[PDB]
Length: 335
Ligand SMILES: O=C([C@@H]1CCN(CCc2ccccc2)C[C@H]1c1ccccc1)N1CCC(O)(Cn2cnc3ccccc3c2=O)CC1
Image (cartoon, rainbow, N blue to C red; front, top):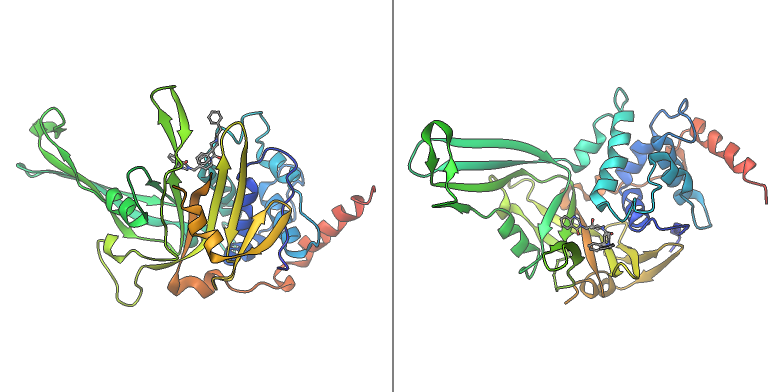
C-alpha cells in the first residue's frame, strides 16, 4: 500500500480510526503543519501533538504511537473513551487546532471544510406567529431504527412534526395553538461527517445498547432534494471516502476503518498496525449489517474532491518543526 498504521497501546477505541480519517483529509493536514507551535510546550500542547502524529504517519516505515497525544488532551480515567462519542473526540481535536490558526494565513480552514447551516422552525396554523432559529453544524446524527437506508434517514430528518391537542404549542401572547414544527438545510459543507445512531437507550435495563440492524449507504449520494434552494452550478452530489466500523459488545469489541484515500474507489483496510488492500464490497456492503458494521460515514462533495484531496510533499512541512522532531527522535535512541 505504502500507507502506515497506528499502534494499539491501550483502550483508545475509535481513536486510531478517527486519526487516519483526518490525516487523509489532505487539505486539513497541510494547514495543521502550518501552525506556529515553535514556542508551545512539548507535553501539554494538543496542536503540537497532532503535528507529530501526522508527520510520523507521513514519514515512518514502522507503526506509529500516540501516548503523547492521549496525554495532551487528558483522557486518562478508566472510562474516558467508553463514556464519549466519536464526534466529541473530533470536536476536542479540531477546536484546539482552529484556535491555534487564528491570526495566520490559514485561519478559518476548519469552518471552510466542515461547517454547514440549518434552520429549525415552528409555525402556527390558525394564527400569525412563526419562530425561526438558525444554527451552524459540524456533523449530523442520523436515525437508523426503522430505516432501510440513508435516503430514508434524511426524509425522516426533514419531517414535519405535528402539534395537536395535549401536544399543542404555547405561542405566548396567543396561548395554546396548533402548529407545524420542522427542520431544513440551507447548506451542506465540502466534507460531510455523518454519525449513525446505533447506541440507544434500553428501557428494559435502564442502559444504552447497540443495534445491529441492516442499514444501506451508497457510494454516491445526491442530496439536492433536501436543500431549501438548489444551484445548477454546484449540485449536492457526494462521494464516499471513509467507513468507520465496529464489531462486538462491552465484553469484546474491535474498531477498524476502511478508506479510499485518493477518492478513486481503491479501498484499504486500516486495523491498528496492519494496513492492507481490500475490495469495494468489503468496505461498503459487508458493513450494512442485518457483528461488523458502520457507525460513521465520511462523504466529500464532488466539486471539491481535488481541492480537499490535494497532494502533499515533504516540502509542505516547515524546517523549524522538522528540526524539533529530529531532536526528540535522537533522545528516543535509548534502545
Ligand atoms: O465506541 C462507542 C461506544 C462506546 C461504548 N460501547 C459499549 C461500552 C458499554 C459498556 C457498558 C455498558 C454498555 C456499553 C458501545 C460503543 C458503540 C459502538 C458502535 C455503535 C454504538 C456504540 N462509540 C463511538 C461511536 C458512536 O459515537 C456512534 N454514535 C454517535 N452518535 C450517536 C448519537 C446518538 C445516538 C447514538 C450515537 C452513536 O452510536 C457511539 C459511541
